[PDB]
Image (tube, helix red, strand yellow):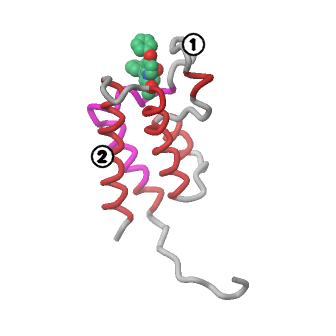
Amino acid sequence: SMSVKKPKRDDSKDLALCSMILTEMETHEDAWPFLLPVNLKLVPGYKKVIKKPMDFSTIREKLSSGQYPNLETFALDVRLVFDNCETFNEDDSDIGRAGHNMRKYFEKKWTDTFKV
Ligand SMILES: CC(=O)c1cc(-c2ccccc2S(C)(=O)=O)c2cc(Oc3ccccc3)ccn12
């Protein structure tokens, strides 16, 4: 509260660390469904069903241009990729499996990087 400062984590390396995580994501063999925005002209349903599309190229651009206020906003966009993937794709399909794999990959890096 006013004039009562809470201790806060050192956030100075967050940008570099999130960039590194995103690079690891981008180069994963199963990243292929997530590299570019879902093609709204070619993918019937997508536009209407998925209210907030997100993908790794969009996140990279946002990260490179100061559009994440903090590391949590970054993680929210990463998780949004995988949440959209699950909404739109069967768990059993190649894309749905890829999404599950990439979510797991991401969360382990997230915990290992930012949870002490
Ligand atoms: C993430 C997702 O739901 C998704 C991703 C693609 C896709 C897959 C392969 C290459 C490129 C893309 S993208 C990001 O350019 O859309 C995809 C494709 C979908 O429908 C198809 C599938 C085959 C042919 C045409 C459209 C549906 C969902 N996604």
Asked if the residue under mark 1 is in contact with the one under mark 2, i.e. CB atoms within 8 Å, the reply is: no
Residue 103 to residue 85: above or below: below
Label 2 secondary element: helix
- Magenta-colored segment: predominant secondary structure: helix
The percent coordinates of residue 29 (x first, y second) are 26, 32
- Nearest to the observer: residue 99 or residue 71: 99
Q: Residue 35: which quarter of the image? A: top left
Tag of residue 92: none
- Please name the residue shown 43% across and 56% down the image: 16
- Nearest to the observer: residue 2 or residue 97: 97
Specify the amino acid type for callout 2.
Answer: Tyr
Q: Cα distance, mark 2 to mark 1? A: 30 Å
Tag of residue 41: 1
Quadrant location, the C terminus: bottom left
Q: Residue 31: which quarter of the image? A: top left
- Please name the residue shown 30% across and 54% down the image: 108
Which quadrant of the picture is home to ligand 1? Answer: top left
- Nearest to the observer: residue 22 or residue 38: 38
- Please name the residue shown 50% across and 41% down the image: 80
Reading the chain from its start, which is encountered first: label 2 or label 1?
1
Q: Which residue lies under the disc numbered 2?
A: 105
The percent coordinates of residue 53 (x first, y second) are 56, 32
Specify the amino acid type for callout 1.
Answer: Lys
- The number of callouts visible is 2
Q: Residue furthest bottom?
A: 4
Specify start and end residues of the magenta stretch as a single range. Answer: 18-37
Label 1 secondary element: loop
The percent coordinates of residue 107 (x first, y second) are 35, 52
Q: Residue 90: which quarter of the image? A: top left
Q: Residues within 10 Å of mark 2 (few under 14, many from 20)?
A: some
